[PDB]
Image 1 (cartoon, helix red, strand yellow):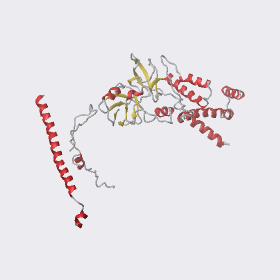
Image 2 (image 1 turned 180 degrees about the horizontal axis):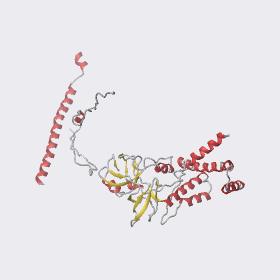
Image 3 (image 1 turned 90 degrees about the vertical axis):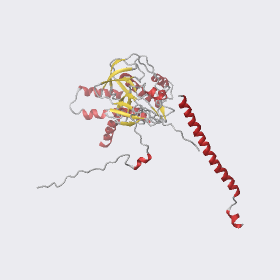
Image 4 (image 1 turned 120 degrees about the vertical axis):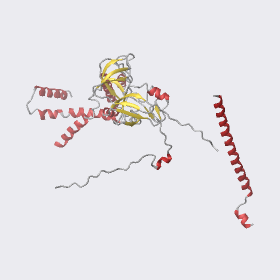
Length: 49
Length: 49
Length: 287
């Protein structure tokens, strides 16, 4: 009863931690894209220059 | 005389569920009874990334 | 000869707990199939705005009627009765049964009721059972609906309104009903209208055909019944081409054949011993 409840709570915390780790890596991808798009001028400016 | 040469019975080809490729969209599970199963419900533990 | 029935919608535990009270009662079904979906079961599929009650009686007369036996997970054990053997029923009718009567089956008259079938509903569907009333009350209330519909064409007068209010009440043993009008807002329902039209026009066709046919018949061997027949016709009157008569006689027969849900009330049960609280009664299925 006690050990199975603590293993179930460990599984809950483990699924939440894996969710948060995936969300952090997707957030790093997203913030890198949003700081790469504010560095990218359009094609006609670079082609003219 | 009136001849009767050959008598032919058609051998119809059998077809089953799991031999058919339609079973790839099916997690085919056999229970025992549904005389008491009024609401046979499955719960889910999906995750949103 | 056992029938099954399944519900497509989610069926709760309260709905089964209020449905299994109706463990042995009549549930008519349109076609004697071995497995029937629940939309066809009952009488909800037939009611609408324009058509009324005599349509329900006429379609229920030609419809087979079965008995509900047991409940399961999502299959319902309907069971068609056989002629001669005896079964048990419940009393959905509002009259206390007694020994040895002859039950009829008529469509229930509380359409949009205060009981509302315990809110045993699904999405745009509801279960409804016909009343099981003994025969004198059955053809009595048939006559009551009929002459309630006859007065409906001139109801602006006030003594006929009190006559209709008398007709709306009823008497039996410890039983008072209030059967509403067929008329709502200065118009009639079409099946009730065609029923009273059929009987009034077969009465008129008799009234203007018997004066021809007593002479077209009585030139054979006359009887005392025939001179008393013309006596009846002549007291009625002094109280005041082949092509047309062939249509008169054809319309006579085919319009009297539209009262067959009224002129013949066919018995469907024979009552045996009854229960205390008078809700249950073993009985013999006839017909």
